[PDB]
Length: 32
Image: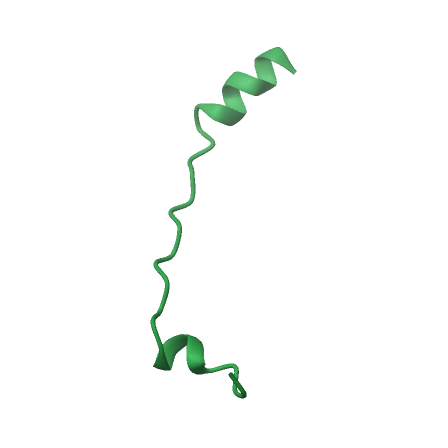
């Protein structure tokens, strides 16, 4: 494409959901 706005004019991709760190950051802090 020529313009960088084709992302919205064409097919927009679904945003990935962020993972929580309440169990991954507290569990890794005890080991590492």
